[PDB]
Amino acid sequence: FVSSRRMFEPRKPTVSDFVQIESCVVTYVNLTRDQLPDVIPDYIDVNKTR
Amino acid sequence: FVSSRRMFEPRKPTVSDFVQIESCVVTYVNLTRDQLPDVIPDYIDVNKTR
Ligand SMILES: *[C@@H]1O[C@H](CO[C@@H]2O[C@@H](C)[C@@H](O)[C@@H](O)[C@@H]2O)[C@@H](O[C@@H]2O[C@H](CO)[C@@H](O)[C@H](O)[C@H]2NC(C)=O)[C@H](O)[C@H]1NC(C)=O
Ligand SMILES: *[C@@H]1O[C@H](CO)[C@@H](O[C@@H]2O[C@H](CO)[C@@H](O)[C@H](O)[C@H]2NC(C)=O)[C@H](O)[C@H]1NC(C)=O
Figure (cartoon, rainbow over the protein chains, first blue to last red):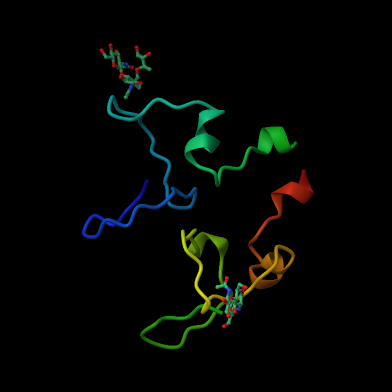
């Protein structure tokens, strides 16, 4: 869930809401190809659509 | 078109500028999926593409 830090406004995540980062860190939740759409309903699997 | 709240700089909107919302309200514009490409040139109908 994503919410304003000031105001609790829980919300589902968005693909555009995120940015890629060069390096992972130990605090990043582990995730897989299949899991990412589960976390992000907005995900687009180009490999599968192709 | 989307433009600054402060001033007038209109341009076509992008799905990247939008977000899901839990609750619809009667103020919201009724819309159809085929209108999404019409409303947003940046929308993609994933199901039909599949
Ligand atoms: C998320 O992943 C990082 C990266 O570690 C790898 O992936 C993990 C799922 C696990 O298989 C690690 O053994 C892999 O090395 C995790 O960071 C690891 O943390 C453990 C804790 O002791 C450490 O032994 C590993 O060396 C770390 N991995 C590194 C440094 O590459 C992390 O714990 C995973 N989970 C979360 C919630 O971030
Ligand atoms: C969009 O669709 C909704 C759902 O039908 C419309 O909401 C209705 O509005 C009328 C107007 O008084 C109410 O009587 C109904 O109770 C509403 N139904 C709901 C909220 O489920 C809405 O008018 C349509 N148009 C717009 C611009 O939202």
